[PDB]
Each structure stands twice: as C-alpha cells, then as structure tokens.
Length: 152
Ligand SMILES: Cn1ccc(C(=O)NC[C@@H]2CCCO2)n1
Image (tube, rainbow, N blue to C red; front, top):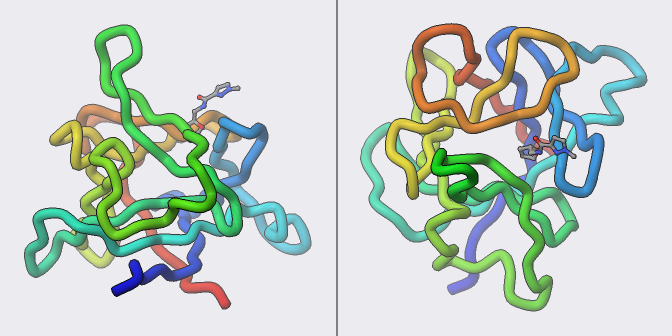
C-alpha cells in the first residue's frame, strides 16, 4: 500500500537541535525556548530495505518539502547532502538507495547508517553551528548518536 511516515525531530547526544540554514544546509546547535520553533521537522518514511530486530530502513525528508537527506560520492568520499525530488513521486516505499538510512537502536539512542555506504553515519560536530555531515566512523570525536521526538 502507501509508504508510512512519521513527523519527528532529532537531537544529538549532546542535545543539539538541527536547523535549516539553507535550501541544502542543516546545522546543529544547542537550542531551548522560543528558538526551538526553528528546529527542522523531518518526515521519516519506513522504506524498503534489509531489516533486523534493531535496524530499520528509513528515508528522512523535510516535513512538507521535496528535500531528502541523501548520500553520494563527492571528492571520492561518501558525503551527506539535501537533494530535491519531484514532489508528485515522493515519498515512496522503494526509495533509491542514496536516500536510505539504517536506523539502528543502540544504548537507548539511535544511529543513522547510510544504506549505500556501510559504516558511514549521520554525524554532528561538538562545536556549535556547524553542518551535519556523514562520518565514516562511530568512534573518535564526531557525534553519531541521536534521540527522536515524535511530533504532531
Ligand atoms: C551551503 N552549505 C555550506 C555547507 C553546506 C553543507 O555542508 N551542506 C550539507 C549538510 C548535510 C545535509 C544538509 O546540509 N551547505
């Protein structure tokens, strides 16, 4: 039938929120109070792909926008971008692989592994107001763990 989706926000494990600074830019910063209205709301779709008890394939679109997180090669490294799509055709159950993330439950948080690029994860920096990016380890100094808030 039709792909199922949920509206949500994400916070990294240092409790930074995500905000849209540009058509193709997401940043992470500490936020509280009225300024939380600035956070990005995602539509998380539950898409086709390999699934296990703790690992579920999803796509992450911006709520009511034809923009999705996707993973592509840039300068011979997996990179994260926002990509526009035809709004008549998305979301769909069979999302192209570059749009798919394995949502992994680990230690009461979530990680988002690229389905296209194994062991590359949606990441944030510890510094304030830096771009979200794809980080090719869950060990060192990038933040790869998140919590989800489910939104009306
Ligand atoms: C205009 N600008 C400067 C830096 C960036 C950037 O890194 N964009 C990518 C991130 C990953 C997902 C969307 O934003 N864009």
